[PDB]
Length: 135
Length: 135
Length: 135
Image 1 (cartoon, each protein chain N blue to C red):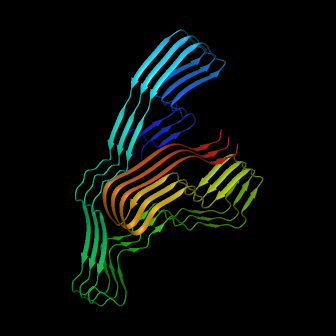
Image 2 (image 1 turned 120 degrees about the vertical axis):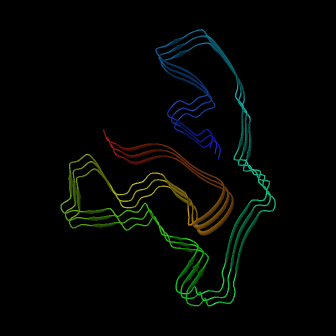
Image 3 (image 1 turned 90 degrees about the horizontal axis):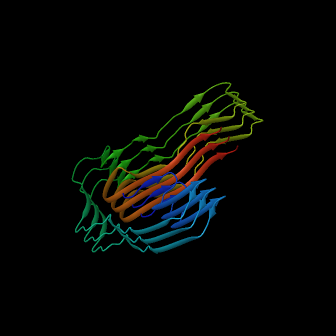
């Protein structure tokens, strides 16, 4: 990727910033800019690319149980949170959070058994995050 | 991608910011910009791409169970949150969250058994987030 | 993508900001801009692209149970939230949230058994989020 930036407050190409109790007095302020940008990005000149898949069967006893190609059974982001109590009590408390499963951004680009991929795959996240503020 | 930016307050090409109790007095302030941008992006001069699948059968005892091509049985983001109590009580409490599955943004681009893919897949998130404010 | 921007308050090309108790007196403020943008994005010069799928059978014992092509049985975002109590009570509390399943944006572009794809897939999210505010 190109020019992926996180800026907290002030982004500028040029900035004049004259803030507090300040005297700014007779000035000549001349500025001659050339700032041209040329991008040739994610550009391709391919001839004859090929993505191919083939299966062929023959004479055999494949009867009781047969699988051809992959078998997938992953457990991902799998949880069994179990809370067992009796006289669970919350009283007079000010800022109380009970959080058994909580999420923010979730990105899954390609999740598969088989993948044939050609080209470009990009995944970008920019963020500012606060879970609790209770002053 | 190009120029994926998170800017918190201000963004500008040129900025003048003359803020508090300031005296700004007699001035010549002169500015000559060329800022041209040329994008050639995600550009593809292909010939003869091919995406191909074939299956061919042959003479056989396949019967009792057969599967041809992949078998998928993942568990993803899979949960069993279990709370057991008797006299569960909340009293006089101010800012109280119970949160057993809670979500913010979810992007799943391709989720599959099989994929044959050519070209470009892009996934972008930009954010500011607070879960609680209760001061 | 190009120019995916998140700006919290002030976006501008040129900005003049003259805020509080400030004196701004005689200025020769002069500005000559060229800011041309040329975009050539997602441009394709393809010839003879082909997407092909075929299945061919022969004489065989396929009668009891047979599957051809992929078999999909994923569990995704699957949950069994179970809460058991006896004398569950909430009294005199101010800002109380019980949330067993809550979501914000959910985007699923392609969820399939098989996919043959050519070209471009883009998924973009931009947000400011607050779950609770109760000061």
